[PDB]
Image (cartoon, helix red, strand yellow):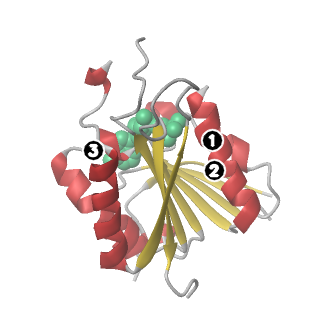
Amino acid sequence: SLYRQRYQFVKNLVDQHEPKKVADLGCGDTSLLRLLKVNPCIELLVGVDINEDKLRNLTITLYHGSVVERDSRLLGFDLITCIELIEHLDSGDLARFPEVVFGYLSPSMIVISTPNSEFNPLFPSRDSDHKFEWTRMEFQTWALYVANRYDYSVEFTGVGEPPAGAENVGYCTQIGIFRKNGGKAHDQHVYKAVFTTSY
Ligand SMILES: C[S@@+](CC[C@H](N)C(=O)[O-])C[C@H]1O[C@@H](n2cnc3c(N)ncnc32)[C@H](O)[C@@H]1O
């Protein structure tokens, strides 16, 4: 339902900008990668996840690894996505996350999605699934800070519109699209490749 919408958001973005090198950080069961490989613009498609069990002309590679460690094999990418990841990082990792993804990796575009804790109406269905949840203001102040620090511009959108009678208090999933200002523009191998294929 909503995960479908998130994936389709990313697919639409890929169709629009045709990135050649795409990485999904916190890729989970690799569903998003499976969807994106459809598009022939992509020449390199990479997934990274700390959960090894979930991972068990075109090159596709899956790495067991953490978003807060610098691996040089993820340098020079066109698009990096972090879909529903940041709300599972503890304060330390959250603090390190931008210096690695924006500072070190420095891709042309980054997409970050996270729940809008203010979403109206809250659908009854747990909060204990993740570490934290952010309001729109919390996400946007964080995202603007990161944007200004690393010389990206950030566009806010999301997926999952309020149902027709509800007061609009944002999308269910809030999304920041970060674009490197000006556009494009030693080996540190840390990740362990779990799977790779090329053809
Ligand atoms: C809520 S799931 C999102 C999965 C996928 N992105 C999606 O939208 O379907 C969060 C994922 O992030 C992974 N993860 C959590 N911390 C991570 C870290 N520090 N480095 C890489 N992956 C991490 C988890 O194992 C999990 O697969």
Measure the alpha-carbon separation of dots 2 and 1.
Answer: 5 Å
2 vs 3, front mark: 2
Instruction: Compute the Cα span from label 2 to label 3.
Output: 22 Å
Name the kind of residue labelled 2 in the image. Answer: Val
- Residue 130, compared with residue 195, is above or below; it is above
Where is 167 relative to 97, above or below? above
User: Of all residues shown, which one is farthest toward the top?
Assistant: 125
- Identify the residue shown where x is 47% and y is 35%: 172
Q: Residue at x 71, y 52 (%)?
A: 12
> As shown in the figure, which amino acid type bears the numbered disc 3?
Leu
Q: How far from the left and from the top, in percent, is residue 45?
A: 64, 57
**Residue at x-position 52% and y-position 31%:** 162
Q: Which quadrant holds the C terminus?
A: bottom right
Dot placed on the residue nearer the N-terminal end, 3 or 1: 1
Q: Is residue 138 left or right of residue 101?
A: left
- Alpha-carbon neighbours of circle 1 within 10 Å: few (<14), some, or many (≥20)? some
Of the numbered discs in the image, which one, if any, rests on residue 10? 2
Q: Nearer the viewer, mark 3 or mark 1?
A: 1
Q: Which mark is residue 89?
A: 3
Q: Earlier in the sequence, mark 2 or mark 3?
A: 2
**Residue hosting label 1:** 7
Q: Is residue 120 left or right of residue 81?
A: left
